[PDB]
Image (tube, coloured by chain):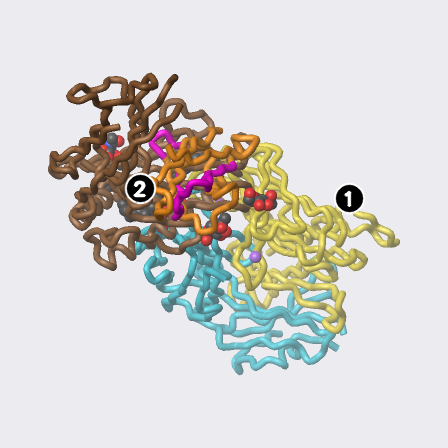
């Protein structure tokens, strides 16, 4: 292909800086655009570079272009959880509608959130309609905890997931487990290495 | 569309038995696609040189063909031009005079 | 006083087939050739690089190489855009360069013909249609004028590159530009009407004077033909006179040319 | 400059006719259709320079394009194939180089539709223990038994969509991972302050938009036709 991005994917921790690269063989090279694409969503333009030696910025994003080297870098300063996305490089071969766009295959960035005050616990939640049906919620563990699939294949366990209570400036991880097959919340997360201080109520 | 004008003329004064150069100058045609043959006795001469095609102030094209030849008492020399503006190839014979 | 002309011809037969060929002239002397078959511009004179360094020439050639490929796709796309207002086959001609004046003065030009008609020029900072151009060309113009990168490059080519380059060429090519080559004449006749022909060949530069003469008397019936080129960058001309048969006697052809140093050619019939 | 696309999501069968539409009110002459597949950049299928103009892009095969007006540019898949499963993007522009992209359309072409099934949706109310331990209340929504995995889960409080304090599984899990036609499950959480959950004027709803059959898709089975539909589950706050 004519447009290559590097790395393919990377994982960083919240607050860290990272650099993404784009190299191309497109001729001629009128301009280069960086897009951010969140999962499922569409294309949000971050910046466009137009000059032989160019530098742009947009908040915590800054970018460079060197047309002689056919090389661009996107720099993200002090990453936040919402930077988790695919970043796409695009070269336009004309300064008009006569141009074709040449898209890179993208760089997948994952930003691990900083959990300040962890409080690991497993809670039992009851169905709003059918009160004898329930799920088990493992929540408030820091980013070091890994959640594993169950031993039993009639027990379901989701991967971890981070929510952000924006107004309270609060983040938390959680995973959910359920089964009908005998099944209780103290047993639910045994296949996982869970913190020793994990609260089990009742 | 415009019809090619053809002018056949020699580089040096013509003398029987003396090597010379024959020129065929094709002008005033459009479009530029054209086929030019120089002929000895109605037969196509092998090593015919062509100048690059160019065009005038008025945008009409022109090109120069030339070849080595030695004029004689008997031999005829011609320039044959095929162009879309003409139904038949136009042939112009070297006058000598 | 010299005109430098870059002449480009392109034929687009259908959506897939095309070729672009260029020739470059300084006055009536060819300096460059760029065939569709060639990746690089060819010098047709030893001095065709002018006063440009190797790095400057390589850079300028590279820009033209990008240009040729880009031009080709652009026309194909503009045809799609205007469809079905215009269809193949299509001829595009460009005539671009600069006329060089005394002092440090010059005027640059870039003229574009479409199917043999002058329709578009670059002027100042943008492309424009000229009088007589069809209105459908306003869309191509708007599209071309959207490209600021091309406009910046063209402005520099025309304002700066062309006159600087041609100044270098005039210095480097001086001895070819100022060459003097002698005309050689000979006489003949054709059909009681007789058309005499004075043939004049091998002269350079172009300015020449040819007349039929009876002694000191200039025959004011002489029809000067066209200037026709020779292959060796010299010129050919013939002058014809219509006379009665038997009236041939005493008639001469006089030729005046700068290579002769006053010593005219006189050939009596 | 705004571009819209419809449908936003589509499940189709092999051999079916699929039409993807793109609308644009910018008075842009030029419109463009692309597909995005993992491992590749967006690739150009067809484009158009105005009403009546359709042009082949880089990968036109299996697609027809239609530009009936300045506003509308359609991508027609006359005989849908599984290889046309992708995310499709439309864009528009004027004489300038900028292309303005629509939000994308996800298409899934299945070999057969026999297993298409909508979700059951259940909402799980916050633990009393969580409330006392944290002063926060986590609601859980579970969508189960659905096929295929083309669902959009959203949370609504008093008829308005909420995003803060939400997280939904990045992908559905397979209920029978040993099967090729396994049904899916998906979970989501909404976390609010205890006092927000305790307020009995707050009405919570987890909604799953499921993409299934159209009204015109043939259905030969006894069970209810698994049409595109919303399934939801609901609860009020309480002291
Ligand atoms: C000129 C005087 C000579 C100087 C003296 C030097 C002497 C050396 C010897 C010369 C030997 C060479 C002889 C060749 C003769 C040619 C002379 C004319 C050359 C003049 C044109 C040069 C343009 C350079 C820029 C350019 O290339 N622009 C391209 C590429 O653009 C992209 O890339 C650049 C960076 O590389 C920038 O990033 C741009 O932003 C980005 O878009 C564009 O696609 C451009 O559009 C190409 C076509 C330009 C052109 O034809 N326009 C003429 C108007 C045509 C009208 C069409 C009408 C039409 C026809 C059919 C249907 C509808 C309409
Ligand atoms: C380049 O020169 C032009 C003016 O020169 C004329 O156009 C050239 C392209 C060429 O054909 C010359 O021989 C001509 O004499 C400048 O154009 C002017 O630009 C200003 C704004 O920048 C504008 O207000 C004027 O109206 C323009 N003149 C005309 C006649 O339209 C141009 O700026 C020069 N560019 C550079 C980069 O030097
Ligand atoms: C296009 O033109 C060329 C040259 O005239 C011709 O040989 C060729 O067959 C044409 N191509 C098509 C697809 O018609
Ligand atoms: C002219 O040159 C281009 C680029 O090298 C090429 O693709 C094309 O086939 C050539 N045309 C002809 C008629 O040879
Ligand atoms: Na555009
Ligand atoms: Na294009
Ligand atoms: Na183009
Ligand atoms: Na793709």
Can residue C145 be seen from the camera position used here? no
Q: Chain of mark 1?
A: D
Nearer the camera: disc 2 or disc 1 = 2
Name the residue beneath numbered marker 2. Answer: B12
Q: Are marks 2 and 1 on the same chain?
A: no
C208 versus C220 height, above or below = below
Can you see residue C137? yes
- Which shade of the palette goes to chain C? brown
**Residue at the image position 61 percent from the left and 65 percent from the top:** D127
Query: Is-magenta flag for residue B58?
Result: yes
Instruction: Determine which of the numbered discs, if any, sits on residue D215 in the image.
Output: 1
Chain holding disc 2:
B
Report if the beta carbon of the residue with label 2 is closer than 8 angstroms to ligand 1. no
Q: Position of residue C142 (x, y in %)?
A: 40, 34
Q: How many neighbours does mark 1 have within 10 angstroms: few (below 14), some (14-19), or many (20 or more)?
A: few
Chain coloured orange in the rendered structure: B
| Coordinates of residue C210 in the picture (x, y in percent) | 23, 28
Q: Out of B6 and C10, give the one closest to the viewer.
A: B6
Image location of residue D34, percent across then percent down: 56, 50
Q: For residue A108: magenta?
A: no
Asked which secondary structure carries label 1, the reply is: loop
Extent of the magenta region? B56-82
Q: Colour of chain A?
A: cyan
Image quadrant where residue A19 sits:
bottom left
Q: Nearer the viewer, residue C123 or C246?
A: C246
Contact check, label 2 and label 1, Cβ < 8 Å: no
Q: What colour do you see for chain D?
A: yellow
Q: Position of residue A23 (x, y in %)?
A: 41, 63
* D36 horizontally vs D227: left or right: left
Location of residue B31 with respect to C196 vertically, above or below: below
Residue lying at 42% horizontally and 61% vertically, measured from the top left:
A24
């Amino acid at each position: 292909t004519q447009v290559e991005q590097s790395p393919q994917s990377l994982v960083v921790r919240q607050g860290e800086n990272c650099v993404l690269q784009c190299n191309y063989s497109v001729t001629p090279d009128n301009h280069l655009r960086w897009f951010k694409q969140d999962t499922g969503k569409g294309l949000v333009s971050l910046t466009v570079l137009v000059d032989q030696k160019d530098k742009t910025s947009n908040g915590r994003y800054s970018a460079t272009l060197d047309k002689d080297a056919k090389h661009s870098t996107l720099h993200i300063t002090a990453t936040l959880l919402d930077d988790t996305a695919t970043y796409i490089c695009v070269v336009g071969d004309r300064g008009s509608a006569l141009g074709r766009l040449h898209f890179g295959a993208g760089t997948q960035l994952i930003v691990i959130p900083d959990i300040q005050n962890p409080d690991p616990a497993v809670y039992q939640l009851r169905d709003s309609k059918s009160s004898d049906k329930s799920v088990c919620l493992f929540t408030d563990f820091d980013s070091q905890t890994n959640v594993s699939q169950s031993k039993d294949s009639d027990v379901y366990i989701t991967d971890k997931c981070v929510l952000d209570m924006r107004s309270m400036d609060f983040k938390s991880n959680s995973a959910v487990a359920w089964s009908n097959k005998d099944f209780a919340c103290a047993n639910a997360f045994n296949n996982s290495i869970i913190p020793e201080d994990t609260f089990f109520p009742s | 569309q415009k019809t090619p004008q053809i002018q056949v003329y020699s580089r040096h004064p013509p003398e029987n038995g003396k090597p010379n150069i024959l020129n065929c100058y094709v002008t005033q045609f459009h479009p530029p696609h054209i086929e030019i043959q120089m002929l000895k006795n109605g037969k196509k001469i092998p090593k015919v040189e062509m100048s690059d095609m160019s065009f005038s102030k008025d945008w009409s094209f022109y090109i120069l063909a030339h070849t080595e030849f030695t004029p004689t008492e008997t031999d005829t020399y011609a320039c044959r031009v095929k162009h879309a503006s003409m139904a038949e190839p136009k042939t112009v014979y070297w006058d000598r005079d | 006083n010299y005109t430098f002309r870059c002449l480009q011809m392109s034929s687009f037969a259908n959506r897939s087939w095309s070729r672009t060929d260029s020739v470059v002239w300084l006055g009536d002397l060819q300096t460059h050739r760029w065939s569709n078959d060639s990746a690089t511009i060819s010098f047709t004179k030893p001095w065709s690089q002018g006063k440009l360094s190797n790095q400057q020439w390589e850079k300028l050639q590279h820009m033209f190489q990008v240009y040729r490929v880009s031009f080709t796709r652009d026309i194909q796309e503009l045809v799609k855009m205007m469809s079905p207002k215009e269809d193949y086959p299509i001829e595009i001609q460009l005539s671009a360069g600069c006329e060089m004046y005394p002092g440090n003065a010059s005027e640059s030009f870039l003229h574009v013909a479409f199917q043999g008609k002058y329709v578009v020029r670059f002027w100042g900072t943008s492309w424009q249609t000229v009088p007589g151009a069809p209105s459908w060309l306003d869309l191509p113009i708007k599209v071309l004028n959207a490209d600021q990168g091309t406009s910046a490059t063209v402005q520099m080519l025309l304002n700066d590159t062309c006159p600087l380059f041609v100044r270098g060429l005039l210095e480097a090519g001086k001895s070819d530009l100022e060459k003097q080559e002698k005309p050689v004449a000979w006489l003949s006749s054709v059909p009681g009407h007789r058309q005499l022909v004075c043939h004049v060949s091998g002269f350079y530069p172009k300015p020449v004077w040819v007349m039929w003469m009876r002694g000191d008397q200039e025959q004011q019936g002489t029809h000067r033909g066209d200037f026709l080129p020779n292959a060796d960058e010299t010129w050919y001309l013939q002058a014809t006179l219509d006379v009665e048969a038997g009236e041939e006697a005493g008639l001469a052809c006089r030729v005046k040319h700068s290579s002769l140093g006053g010593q005219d050619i006189i050939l009596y019939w | 400059a705004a571009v819209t696309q419809s449908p936003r999501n589509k499940v189709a069968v092999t051999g079916g006719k699929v039409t993807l539409s793109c609308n644009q009110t910018n008075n842009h002459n030029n419109m463009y259709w692309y597909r995005q597949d993992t491992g590749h950049g967006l690739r150009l299928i067809h484009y158009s320079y105005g009403a009546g103009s359709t042009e082949k892009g880089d990968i036109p095969d299996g697609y027809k394009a239609s530009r009936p007006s300045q506003e509308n540019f359609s991508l027609i898949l006359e005989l849908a194939t599984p290889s046309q499963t992708s995310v499709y993007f439309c864009a528009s522009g004027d004489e300038g180089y900028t292309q303005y992209f629509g939000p994308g359309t996800r298409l899934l072409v299945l070999e057969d539709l026999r297993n298409v099934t909508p979700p059951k949706v259940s909402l799980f109310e916050p633990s009393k223990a969580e409330i006392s331990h944290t002063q926060k209340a986590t609601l859980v929504c579970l969508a189960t038994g659905f096929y295929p995995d083309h669902v959009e889960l959203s949370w609504w409080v008093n008829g308005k969509e909420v995003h803060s304090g939400v997280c939904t599984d990045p992908q559905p899990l397979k209920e029978q991972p040993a099967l090729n036609d396994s049904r899916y499950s998906l979970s989501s959480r909404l976390r609010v302050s205890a006092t927000f959950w305790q307020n009995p004027r707050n009405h919570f709803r987890c909604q799953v938009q499921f993409y299934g059959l159209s009204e015109n898709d043939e259905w030969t089975q006894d069970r209810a036709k698994p049409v595109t539909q919303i399934v939801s589950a609901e609860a009020w706050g309480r002291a």
